[PDB]
Image (cartoon, rainbow over all chains, first blue to last red; front, side, top):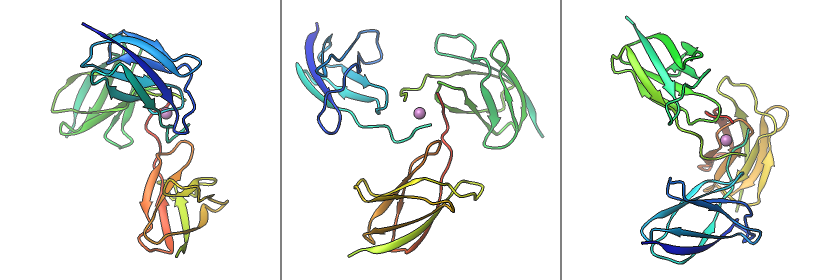
Length: 80
Length: 80
Length: 80
Ligand code: NI
């Protein structure tokens, strides 16, 4: 009923994003990336992940039945 | 030439948002929500209100000739 | 192969924005506005400038072969 997605989150230069939130859709099922930018989450194969971290644009990525995902976060384009 | 709109502003859990700005369109006619999430503003019946508060997505809501309005603010999806 | 664009950056009231970033597209070719809101940048005539400054919405403006440009920045509509 789920698959286990193992993912890697980087910035545009390919450096790991450490501590990014990775949540299944808008549910309470979520995790954080580790010291290497890696996460593991059990999700529906047809779901989408929301990835966020301070200083970056939040992104929604479709799982598309993939057990391995790479997410490249882009920096925010404003500050206060 | 106006109506008086009495409104209630909440977050997604239904708790009042206290101190939110409620402005007629982009004009200088504005107020703030009280301790109970309530506001009163005199506006054109055909106008729209802009509702904002720190930490939430600004929203525009059509008055649609209504003298009683509920606004549900959603949290921002980034931070810095 | 380039033109020199001389530009003036203001807020909605017409006051200079001092220290705004002015970058050719998403490249490393960039400058900042001076004490009078003015910048000079050498760019492709067919390019676009990205103008940003704390507290304002980032804007992209086409050069359109113009050697003189005015940019009016609008304030951000949220804060944290
Ligand atoms: Ni922000």
